[PDB]
Image (cartoon, grey):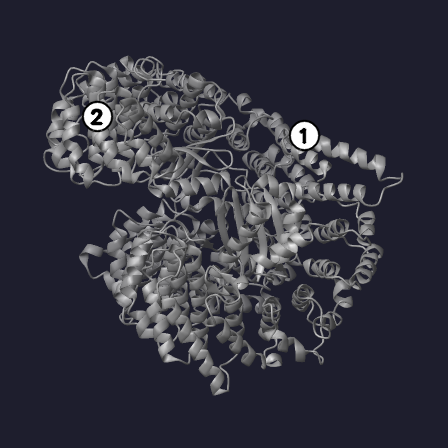
C-alpha cells in the first residue's frame, strides 16, 4: 500500500501532503523533517529506494520538488517509481508547465488529480489518456 | 558536449574565462573530467591569476588520479626555477599537494634546492612541503637527511620560517622510537625564547606548544624560562594566554615554599586568566573548561575571584553550566549566602538540565559545609514539595549523597522520601532511593513492601540498579533476619539463574557463599562501618587530571577525556 | 479565474518574518469576526472563497479549530466547484462532534442518491479519504450493491471497489460475507481494464486476509495475464506504457497469484508456466526502445514474475532461469537494478533448489561489496552474504565481513559486528578461531561493538573448558599491547582473573606482572570496568597468596576506599574485610569453581531480531 | 592542525569545501549536514565529536561555518582562526550572505589556499594579503 505522498521543496516546505491513515499533529512535522533530511543528503549516483525504520520511500528529483512516496516493504519498487513518473507526466501535459508556484496556486487541482489516481493507498488509474479526458471534461462546466 | 566546444578556445582571455567557468562548475557540482587534457594543454602560460586557477584545478582533480598526472613533474620542475619567488612557492606547494607513491622518487632531488635559498617565504613554503611529505610515504633513508636539513634550518633570522619549521618538527615528532627529537638543549631553548620574543602571534603559539615537553635539569633554568614566558598576555585571547598558562603550570615543579617567586607567579596567573571571560562565547567556553581543570588541579589561585563567575542572563547554556560548577568549585565559608541566593534564583528557571544541575549544585554546596548543609536540606525539602519530577529525582540523588556524607543526622526526611516513590524513572534515582531504603532499614518497617515492589521486574533494567537492589536486600536481611528469607532467596535465584551478566552472577555468588557460611562474618563484612567521604564533590581521578595538565590547550581539556580515547 | 486567492498567494507568500504573518492572521481573525459573526452571507462565491482561503491558511502550516458548520452547509449544492471545495475541506480537517457529524452523514446520504458519475465519485472519494465510525456503520453493506447489483459507469465502480478496500481495512468487523461475491470476482474480466485494476487490488487484499473465500479467481486471473503478456504490440494503445503491455496490471495480477498455492488444475499451472517462459524470453531480447523508463517497466514486471516463481518453488527450470537472470543483473550499469537484484537474491537464497547456484555468485557479491562503495547496496550485499552462509566458506566470509567492518562508517559497524558475532558463534568447529575472531572484533571496532557480545564470549570461554587456556594466553599477550580498548579491559580482567593458574607457569607471565598490568589499566576506565577489576583483584587474593600483600596495599588507599561511587566503596570495603579476616577457610570456601553457564536464551539472536524493523 | 574546512547554507547546502587531509572525505560532509544542522536537539556545544572526529562550527548571519579535524589540535587555535577569517571576509566584502559567498568562489578559494596550508594558519594581519591577492 501507499502510506503517504509528498512534494517537498528545496527548503523543506510541503507543497502537497496526502496521508492514508491517521497521524498526529507533531508526527506529521517529524515525518516531514526526517524525510527531508533523508532525501536532501543523497546525490545523483545513489539508489532511489532508501528505507528508514519500517518503511521505504520512492523519491525522484524534478526541478525543485522531491516527489516522495512511502510504501510497505513487500511492494515492488520499480512499479511505484514508474507510477510517480506517470503522475509527474500527467501534471506536465495537464498544466502544460510544471512549477511550484502553479502547484501552490491550484492546490485543489493537485488534490483532485491525486484522488483521481490514488485512493485508499493503491493505484486507481494508470493511463494518461482517460484521466486527461475525464479531467478536461469537467473543466468546461 | 557544449562545455568542450566553449572551452576549446584560441583567445587567451576566453581561455581564462573558460577556466573560471570550469572552477565554478566544479564548485556547483558539474563534472568536466573529460576536459582535463585541454586544461593541461592550456596550463602552458605566464599569467599569475590563471596560474593559480589552473593549480587549484590541478590539485582538485589530479588528487584523484596519478596516472596521466605523472607527466606534470617536468612542468613542475620547469616552474620551480622561474626567478620570481611567489610562483616558485606556489608551484612547490601544489607539487607536494599530490599524495601518491610515484611522486616521491621524482621530487626527492628537486626539493633539496628549495630548502637552501635566500628567501623567507620560499623557505617557509619548503618547510611546510617537507611536513606535507613526511605525513605519507616518507620514511626512507635520505628522509633523515631532509629532517636534519629542516632541523638545522631553525638557524634563520626570519620569525615566520623558524616558527613554521618548529611547528612542522613538533607535528612530525609523534613517532617515538625512544629517540625524542634529539634537540632543544639549553642554547636552543634560549634561541627559541628569543624568537618567541621576535615572532608573530601564530609562531608564538607554535613555540609555546612545542616547549611543553622539556624537563628542566635545575631550578635556575626553570626560573629563567618562567620570567621569559610571563610577558605573554596578548590580544590573541585564548590561544597565547592558555598556551602560556599550560607551560607555566607544567614548569611548577620547584618547591612550593621557596624564595618569593612562587607566590608572585601564582598571583600573575589570575588577572589574564579571568580576563579571558570577556571574549567571544566559544573562546569563553574553552577558557571556562580550562579554568575548571586548573581550579580542580590547583585550587589556591581563583580564591577571591568568585564574583566574576556569577551567571548572567544573556549567557548561552554551556557557558551557564560551566560557570555554575566553577562557582561551586570556588564556593567556601565566606560566600555561602550569595551563592545560595543565586542558586535559589536559578532553581526557578525553565531550562531543564540547567535546573537539574542547579539543584545538584545546591546539594553539593550542602555537601561542602554544614550550615550550607542544613539550609540546602531545607531548600531541597521545598523543591521536593514543588512536586516537579526531574527536580525530585535530582534531589533524591543529592539526598543519598548527603546521607553518605553525614551519618545519622537527617533521618527525619526518609519518611518524606518514601512518600513519593512512584515518580522515579531514571536508573540513578532508583538506585539512590533503593540504597537509602536499604541502609536505613531499621527505622522503616515498610521497606519490605518497597523492595518487593522493585522486585517485580528484575530483568529489562539497568545492571547498576540490579546490583544496588541486591546489596540493599542483603543488608536488609542481615538487619532483619527473622522474616526475610523469601526475598533473599528470590533475589539470589534471579541473580544466579537468569541474569546474563557475569558481573551480576559474580555478586550473587559472592553473597550466596557468605550468607550460608557464618552470620558473624556476614555481619562484620557487609555491615562494616564505612568511613567518611571527605569532599568527593565531582572530582576527576588524580592520575587522569595529572595527565590532562600536559594538554591544557588541546581538545583533551575541552572534552575532559584523554587523547588516547579519541584519535 | 478567481482574483482573491491569487492576490492572497502573491502577497502573503512574499513577506517578512513570522511576526508579519502572525499580524496578518490576526487581521484575518478581525475580518472573520466582522463578517461571519452575524450579517448575511452569500451562497456560492463568498463561501467558496473564504473556505478555500482557510484551507490554504491551514496548508501553510497554521491551525484552525472552527468555521466548518457553515462550510459543511455547502455540501448540498448544484455547482461542481462548490461541492468539491466542501468535500475537500471536510476531508482535510476532522473534528470530534455529534450533531455536525450526523449532519455530514445526512448530507452525504442525500448526495449519494444522485444520477451522475461525478457526484457519486466525489461522495465515494470523501468516504474513502478519511473514514469514520459513522461512515463505517452507515456505509458497510450498501456499497456492494453499487458494485455488484448495478450496471453503472466504470469510475463509480472503481471508487466503490476502493471504498470497500478502505472500509475492510479500517473496520473488518461489520462487513458481511453474504451472497454478493458471485459477480465481484466475476467482473475481473470486464472491459476497460480499470475496473480490473480496482477489483484486482480489492480481491488481493481480501485473499491476503481471507484466502479461501475467492479461490475461483485463479482461472480468470491467469487467462487475463496470458492475454495481456502476448496479444499484440499495438493492441489497446491506451493502456500501453512505453511499448510495455500493462506493467501495473500485470504486477497486480502477479501479486494476486502469489497469495494462493499452485492451482490444482494442471491446465492452469501449464498456462502459468507458458506465460512465465514468455515473460522471461521477452525480457531476454534487447530493448525495443532506448528510453530508461521502458527498461524500468520491463524489469518491474520481470521482478514480479521472479518473485512469483520464488514463492511457488515448484519449477526447477524457472528457478535456474531466474538465477541466471539475477547473475546477469548483478553487473548491470543501473544502480537501481543492482540493488533490486541483490534484494531479490537475498530473498531467493532460502530456496534449497538454488542454494548452490546462489553460492556460485559469491565472488561477484564480494566484488560488488568492495566496488560500489554505497551504503544501502553494501548493506544488501552483507545481508546476502549472511544469507548464503552454509559452513563451506566460514573463514573467507568472516574475513570479508571483518574487512568491511574495517571500512564502515557509523552504524553498519554495529550491524556487522552483531552479525559477525552470531555467525562465528554458530558456525565454528575449532573454537580457538572463535576466540581469535572475537578479539579481532574487539580490537577493530571496540567503541561500537555491543553490550551482549562480551557476555556471550565470557559464557563460551567459561562453558567450553578446553579452550580456556588459549583464551587466557591470547588475552594476556593482547593486553600489554599499546592498543587496548575498554571492552578488551573488561574481558581480559574477567578471563585472566578466572584462569590465571593456567598461565602462571610461564615466568614471562608471573602474577605480579599480571596484577601490575591490570592496575595500570585500572586508573583510566569507567565505573563498571573498575568494579570488574576489583572482583578480579579479590579472585587473585584467593588464587595468588604471593601477591596478597601488594593487593591489600592497593585497595586500602583513600582513593579506592573513600571513593565517590557507592559500588566501588562497597566492593572495596567488602573485599578488604574479607582479606583482613583471612581465616584461610571461609575465603577459599566462598570463591568456588563457579560452574559453567547454562544455555539460557542466546540473547544475541533476540537482540538482532529486535533490531530488525 | 585544521583538516577540512566547510561553509554551509541556511537550508543545508554546501557552498565551498576545501580539504587538506586524506582523512577528511564526504563522510565529514554527511555527518555535519545530518547531525548538526538537521539535528532536532537545539541544546548542543560548539565542539561535537562524531566517530572520533571533532566538528567545530561558528554561526555568523545565516551560514554554518565549520572546521573539521581528526587530531587533538588546540581549540583556541581553530576558534580564533575562524574569527579572524570571518573578520577578513567582512573586510573584503562587507556583510556575509549566500550570494556574497556564491559570487566570489574564486576569491574565497584563493584566500583559503593562501591563508592556510595543510592546517597551519600562517598570517592574517593585513600586511601580506594586500600585496599579492587579486580582486
Counting labels gives: 2
Is A118 rendered above or below residue D27?
Answer: below
Q: Secondary structure at mark 2?
A: helix
Residue drawn 31% across the image and 60% down it: C331
Q: Is residue C173 visible?
A: yes
- Residue D132 appears in which quarter of the rendering? top left
Label 1 and label 2 in one chain? no
Query: Mark 1 Cα within 10 Å, few/some/many (few <14, many 20+)?
Result: few
Q: Which label is found at residue B82?
A: none
Query: Mark 2 Cα within 10 Å, few/some/many (few <14, many 20+)?
Result: many
The chain under label 2 reads B
On the rendered structure, is B46 left or right of B396? left
Q: List the residue tagged with mark 2.
A: B91
Q: Nearer the viewer, residue C306 or C246?
A: C246
Instruction: Give the Cα distance between marks 1 and 2.
Output: 55 Å
On the rendered structure, is C247 left or right of B356? left
Horizontal and vertical percent position of residue D133? 32, 17
- Residue A4 appears in which quarter of the rendering? bottom right
Horizontal and vertical percent position of residue D60? 49, 26
The chain under label 1 reads C
Q: Nearer the viewer, residue B288 or D71?
A: D71
Q: Secondary structure at mark 1?
A: helix
Residue drawn 31% across the image and 52% down it: C406
- Residue B566 appears in which quarter of the rendering? top left
Q: List the residue tagged with mark 1.
A: C19
On the rendered structure, is C417 left or right of C48? left
Amino acid at each position: 500500500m501507499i502510506r503517504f505522498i509528498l512534494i517537498q521543496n528545496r527548503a523543506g516546505k510541503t507543497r502537497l501532503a496526502k496521508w492514508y491513515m491517521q497521524f498526529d499533529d507533531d508526527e506529521k512535522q517529524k515525518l516531514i523533517e526526517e524525510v527531508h533530511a533523508v532525501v536532501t543528503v543523497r546525490d545523483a549516483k545513489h539508489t532511489n529506494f532508501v528505507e528508514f525504520r519500517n518503511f521505504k520511500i520512492i523519491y525522484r528529483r524534478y526541478a525543485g520538488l522531491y516527489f516522495c512516496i512511502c510504501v510497505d516493504v513487500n511492494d515492488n519498487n520499480l512499479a511505484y517509481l514508474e507510477a510517480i513518473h506517470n503522475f509527474v507526466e500527467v501534471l506536465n501535459e495537464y498544466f502544460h508547465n510544471v512549477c511550484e508556484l502553479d502547484l501552490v496556486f491550484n492546490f485543489y487541482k493537485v488534490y483532485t488529480v491525486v484522488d483521481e489516481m490514488f485512493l485508499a493507498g493503491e493505484i486507481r488509474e494508470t493511463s494518461q489518456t482517460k484521466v486527461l479526458k475525464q479531467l478536461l471534461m469537467l473543466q468546461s462546466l | 558536449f557544449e562545455l568542450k566546444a566553449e572551452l576549446n578556445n584560441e583567445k587567451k582571455e576566453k581561455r581564462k574565462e573558460a577556466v573560471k567557468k570550469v572552477i565554478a562548475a566544479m564548485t556547483v557540482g558539474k563534472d568536466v573530467s573529460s576536459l582535463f587534457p585541454d586544461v593541461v594543454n592550456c596550463m602552458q602560460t605566464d599569467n599569475l591569476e590563471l596560474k593559480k586557477l589552473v593549480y587549484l584545478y590541478l590539485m582538485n582533480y589530479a588528487k584523484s588520479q596519478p596516472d596521466m598526472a605523472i607527466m606534470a613533474v617536468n612542468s613542475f620542475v620547469k616552474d620551480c626555477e622561474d626567478p620570481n619567488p611567489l610562483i616558485r612557492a606556489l608551484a612547490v606547494r601544489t607539487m607536494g599537494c599530490i599524495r601518491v607513491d610515484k611522486i616521491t622518487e621524482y621530487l626527492c632531488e628537486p626539493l633539496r634546492k628549495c630548502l637552501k635559498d635566500e628567501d623567507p617565504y620560499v623557505r617557509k613554503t619548503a618547510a611546510v612541503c617537507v611536513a606535507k611529505l613526511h605525513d605519507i610515504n616518507a620514511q626512507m633513508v635520505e628522509d633523515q637527511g631532509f629532517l636534519d636539513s629542516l632541523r638545522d634550518l631553525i638557524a634563520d633570522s626570519n620569525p615566520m620560517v623558524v616558527a613554521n619549521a618548529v611547528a612542522a618538527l613538533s607535528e612530525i615528532s609523534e613517532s617515538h622510537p625512544n629517540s625524542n627529537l634529539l634537540d632543544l638543549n639549553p642554547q636552543n631553548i634560549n634561541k627559541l625564547l628569543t624568537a618567541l620574543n621576535e615572532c608573530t602571534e601564530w609562531g608564538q603559539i607554535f613555540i609555546l606548544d612545542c616547549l611543553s615537553n622539556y624537563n628542566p635539569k635545575d631550578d635556575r633554568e626553570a626560573q629563567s624560562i618562567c620570567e621569559r614566558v610571563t610577558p605573554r598576555l596578548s590580544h590573541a585571547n585564548s590561544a597565547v594566554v592558555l598556551s602560556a598558562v599550560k607551560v607555566l603550570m607544567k614548569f611548577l615543579e620547584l618547591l612550593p615554599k621557596d624564595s618569593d617567586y612562587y607566590n608572585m607567579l601564582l598571583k600573575k596567573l589570575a588577572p589574564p586568566l579571568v580576563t579571558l571571560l570577556s571574549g567571544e562565547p566559544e573562546v569563553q567556553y574553552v577558557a571556562l573548561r580550562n579554568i575548571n581543570l586548573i581550579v580542580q588541579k590547583r585550587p589556591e589561585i581563583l580564591k577571591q575571584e568568585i564574583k566574576v563567575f556569577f551567571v548572567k542572563y544573556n549567557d548561552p547554556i554551556y557557558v551557564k553550566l560551566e560557570k555554575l560548577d566553577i562557582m561551586i568549585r570556588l564556593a567556601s565559608q565566606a560566600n555561602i549566602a550569595q551563592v545560595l541566593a543565586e542558586l535559589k534564583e536559578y532553581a526557578t528557571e525553565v531550562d531543564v538540565d540547567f535546573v537539574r544541575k542547579a539543584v545538584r549544585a545546591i546539594g553539593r554546596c550542602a555537601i561542602k559545609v554544614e550550615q550550607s548543609a542544613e539550609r540546602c536540606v531545607s531548600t531541597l525539602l521545598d523543591l521536593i514539595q514543588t512536586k516537579v519530577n526531574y527536580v525530585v529525582q535530582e534531589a533524591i540523588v543529592v539526598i543519598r549523597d548527603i546521607f553518605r556524607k553525614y551519618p545519622n543526622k537527617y533521618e527525619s526526611i526518609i519518611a518524606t522520601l518514601c512518600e513519593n516513590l512512584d515518580s522515579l524513572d531514571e536508573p540513578d534515582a532508583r538506585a539512590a532511593m533503593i540504597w537509602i531504603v536499604g541502609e536505613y532499614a531499621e527505622r522503616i518497617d515498610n521497606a519490605d513492601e518497597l523492595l518487593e515492589s522493585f522486585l517485580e521486574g528484575f530483568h529489562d533494567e539497568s545492571t547498576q540498579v540490579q546490583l544496588t537492589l541486591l546489596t540493599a536486600i542483603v543488608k536488609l536481611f542481615l538487619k532483619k533476619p527473622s522474616e526475610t528469607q523469601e526475598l533473599v532467596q528470590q533475589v539470589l535465584s534471579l541473580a544466579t539463574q537468569d541474569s546474563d551478566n557475569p558481573d551480576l552472577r559474580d555478586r550473587g555468588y559472592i553473597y550466596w557463599r557468605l550468607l550460608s557460611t557464618d552470620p558473624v562474618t556476614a555481619k562484620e563484612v557487609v555491615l562494616s562501618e564505612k568511613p567518611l567521604i571527605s569532599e568527593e564533590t565531582d572530582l576527576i581521578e588524580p592520575t587522569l587530571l595529572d595527565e590532562l595538565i600536559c594538554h591544557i590547550g588541546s581538545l583533551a581539556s575541552v572534552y575532559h577525556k584523554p587523547p588516547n580515547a579519541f584519535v | 479565474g478567481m482574483r482573491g486567492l491569487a492576490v492572497f498567494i502573491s502577497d502573503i507568500r512574499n513577506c517578512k518574518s513570522k511576526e508579519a504573518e502572525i499580524k496578518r492572521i490576526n487581521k484575518e481573525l478581525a475580518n472573520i469576526r466582522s463578517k461571519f459573526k452575524g450579517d448575511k452571507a452569500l451562497d456560492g462565491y463568498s463561501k467558496k472563497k473564504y473556505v478555500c482561503k482557510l484551507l490554504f491558511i491551514f496548508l501553510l502550516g497554521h491551525d484552525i479549530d472552527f468555521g466548518h458548520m457553515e462550510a459543511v452547509n455547502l455540501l448540498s449544492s448544484n455547482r461542481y466547484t462548490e461541492k468539491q471545495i466542501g468535500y475537500l475541506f471536510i476531508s482535510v480537517l476532522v473534528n470530534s462532534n455529534s450533531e455536525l457529524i450526523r449532519l455530514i452523514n445526512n448530507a452525504i446520504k442525500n448526495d449519494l442518491a444522485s444520477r451522475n458519475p461525478t457526484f457519486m465519485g466525489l461522495a465515494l472519494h470523501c468516504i474513502a479519504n478519511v473514514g469514520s465510525r459513522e461512515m463505517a456503520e452507515a456505509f458497510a453493506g450498501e456499497i456492494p450493491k453499487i458494485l455488484v447489483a448495478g450496471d453503472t459507469m466504470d469510475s463509480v465502480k472503481q471508487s466503490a471497489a476502493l471504498c470497500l478496500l478502505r472500509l475492510y481495512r479500517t473496520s473488518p468487523d461489520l462487513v458481511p460475507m453474504g451472497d454478493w461475491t458471485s459477480r465481484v470476482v466475476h467482473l475481473l474480466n470486464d472491459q476497460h481494464l480499470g475496473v480490473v485494476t480496482a477489483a484486482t487490488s480489492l480481491i488481493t487484499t481480501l485473499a491476503q486476509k481471507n484466502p479461501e473465500e475467492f479461490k475461483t479467481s485463479v482461472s480468470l486471473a491467469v487467462s487475463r495475464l496470458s492475454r495481456i503478456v502476448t496479444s499484440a504490440s499495438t493492441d489497446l494503445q491506451d493502456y500501453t506504457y512505453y511499448f510495455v503491455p500493462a506493467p501495473w496490471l500485470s504486477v497486480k495480477l502477479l501479486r494476486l497469484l502469489q497469495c494462493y498455492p499452485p492451482p490444482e488444475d494442471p491446465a492452469v499451472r501449464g498456462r502459468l508456466t507458458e506465460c512465465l517462459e514468455t515473460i522471461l524470453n521477452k525480457a531476454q531480447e534487447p530493448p525495443k526502445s532506448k528510453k530508461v523508463q521502458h527498461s524500468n517497466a520491463k524489469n518491474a514486471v520481470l521482478f514480479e514474475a521472479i518473485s512469483l516463481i520464488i514463492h511457488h518453488d515448484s519449477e526447477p527450470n524457472l528457478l535456474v532461469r531466474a538465477c541466471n537472470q539475477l547473475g546477469q543483473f548483478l553487473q548491470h550499469r543501473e544502480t537501481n537494478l543492482r540493488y533490486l537484484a541483490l534484494e531479490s537474491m537475498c530473498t531467493l537464497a532460502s530456496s534449497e533448489f538454488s542454494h548452490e547456484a546462489v553460492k556460485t555468485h559469491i565472488e561477484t557479491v564480494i566484488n560488488a561489496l568492495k566496488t560500489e562503495r554505497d551504503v544501502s547496496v553494501r548493506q544488501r550485499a552483507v545481508d546476502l552474504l549472511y544469507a548464503m552462509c552454509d559452513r563451506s566458506n566460514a573463514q573467507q566470509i568472516v574475513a570479508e565481513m571483518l574487512s568491511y567492518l574495517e571500512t564502515a562508517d557509523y552504524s553498519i559497524r554495529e550491524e556487522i559486528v552483531l552479525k559477525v558475532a552470531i555467525l562465528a558463534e554458530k558456525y565454528a568447529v575449532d573454537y580457538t578461531w572463535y576466540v581469535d575472531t572475537i578479539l579481532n572484533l574487539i580490537r577493530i571496532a571496540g567503541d561500537y561493538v555491543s553490550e551482549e557480545v562480551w557476555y556471550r564470549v565470557i559464557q563460551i570461554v567459561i562453558n567450553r573448558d578446553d579452550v580456556q587456556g588459549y583464551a587466557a594466553k591470547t588475552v594476556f599477550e593482547a593486553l600489554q599491547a599499546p592498543a587496548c580498548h575498554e571492552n578488551l579491559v573488561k574481558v581480559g580482567g574477567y578471563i585472566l582473573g578466572e584462569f590465571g593458574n593456567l598461565i602462571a607457569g610461564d615466568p614471562r607471565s608471573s602474577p605480579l606482572i599480571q596484577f601490575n598490568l591490570l592496575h595500570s589499566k585500572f586508573h583510566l576506565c569507567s565505573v563498571p570496568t573498575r568494579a570488574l577489576l576489583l572482583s578480579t583483584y579479590i579472585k587473585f587474593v584467593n588464587l595468588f597468596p604471593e601477591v596478597k600483600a601488594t593487593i591489600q596495599d592497593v585497595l586500602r588507599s583513600d582513593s579506592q576506599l573513600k571513593n565517590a561511587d557507592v559500588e566501588l566503596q562497597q566492593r572495596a570495603v567488602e573485599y578488604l574485610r574479607l582479606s583482613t579476616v583471612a581465616s584461610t577457610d571461609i575465603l577459599a570456601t566462598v570463591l568456588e569453581e563457579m560452574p559453567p553457564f547454562p544455555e539460557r536464551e542466546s540473547s544475541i539472536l533476540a537482540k538482532l531480531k529486535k533490531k530488525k524493523g | 592542525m585544521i583538516g577540512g574546512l566547510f561553509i554551509y547554507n541556511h537550508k543545508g547546502e554546501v557552498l565551498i569545501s576545501r580539504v587538506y587531509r586524506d582523512d577528511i572525505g564526504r563522510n565529514a560532509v554527511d555527518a555535519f549536514r545530518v547531525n548538526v544542522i538537521h539535528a532536532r536537539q537545539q541544546v548542543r556545544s560548539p565542539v561535537t565529536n562524531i566517530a572520533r572526529t571533532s566538528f567545530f562550527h561558528v554561526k555568523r548571519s545565516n551560514i554554518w561555518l565549520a572546521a573539521v579535524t581528526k587530531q587533538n589540535v588546540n581549540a583556541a587555535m581553530v576558534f580564533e582562526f575562524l574569527y579572524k577569517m570571518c573578520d577578513v571576509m567582512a573586510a573584503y566584502f562587507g556583510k556575509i550572505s549566500e550570494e556574497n559567498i556564491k559570487n566570489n568562489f574564486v576569491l574565497i578559494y584563493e584566500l583559503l589556499d593562501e591563508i592556510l596550508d595543510f592546517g597551519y594558519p600562517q598570517n592574517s594581519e593585513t600586511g601580506a594579503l594586500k600585496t599579492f591577492i587579486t580582486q
